[PDB]
Image (spheres, rainbow, N blue to C red):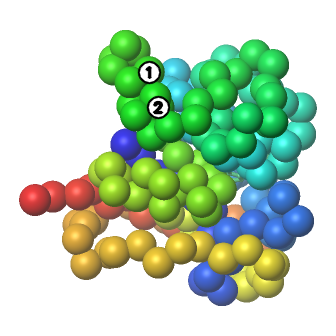
Amino acid sequence: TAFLWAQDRDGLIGKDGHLPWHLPDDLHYFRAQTVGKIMVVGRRTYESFPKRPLPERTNVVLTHQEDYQAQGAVVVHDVAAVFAYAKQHPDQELVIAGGAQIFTAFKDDVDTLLVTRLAGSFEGDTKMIPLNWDDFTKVSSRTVEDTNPALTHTYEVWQKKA
Ligand SMILES: COc1cc(NCc2ccc3[nH+]c(N)nc(N)c3c2C)cc(OC)c1OC
């Protein structure tokens, strides 16, 4: 599995559904880390989208309620159903974008950890869960400085090893 969430040093991850800061570059990297692979999102992250569903990519939704409905999307209701669908499609991959409940839902079968740190401080309402970094190892990284110092961030790429 692969994780990917945008959080700032203030332990933030989002705010009012959309993000608290404006990072056009990070918003363009999402389309690059979603096409070709399966995009797994929760119900709060689904409606949080602008013009859903997202085309050019799979749209899965994990929910334990028989009331939520999604037209043109694989509504899964079990962790085995999400992994069972990935087995039939080996050409694609599993990627977690949110919400916080979806991350901890697949935190057990997690492998890669793509975290986007931002130098600019931003306060919101939702925070990121406590990941066990004492069980991972760095392998690659990509630093990038925007026009404003606060708009500075770095894509850290870690890999599980045991
Ligand atoms: C306000 O603009 C937008 C906001 C969001 N919010 C969710 C969001 C934002 C950045 C993200 N960045 C990375 N690295 N990975 C994610 N998983 C991710 C997600 C899940 C998502 C958008 O497209 C889906 C979008 O349009 C650009």
At x 80%, y 63%, the residue is 19
* Residue displayed at 32% across by 75% down: 133
* Above-or-below relation of 73 to 105: above
Identify which amino acid the numbered label 1 is placed on.
Tyr
Residue 25, disc: none
Q: Position of residue 66 (x, y in %)?
A: 73, 35
Q: Quadrant of the C terminus?
A: bottom left
**Amino acid marked by disc 2:** Val
Q: Nearer the viewer, residue 113 or 145?
A: 113
Element type at mark 1: helix
Say above or below: 124 vs 111.
Answer: below
Residue 60 position within the rendered picture, expressed as x and y whole percent measured from the top left: 62, 30
Q: Which mark is residue 82?
A: 2
Is 63 placed above or below 56 here?
A: below
Q: For residue 88, say whether it is visible.
A: yes
Quadrant location of the N terminus?
top left
Residue to which mark 1 is pinned: 85
How many residues crowd around disc 1 within 10 Å: few (fewer than 14), some, or many (20 or more)?
some
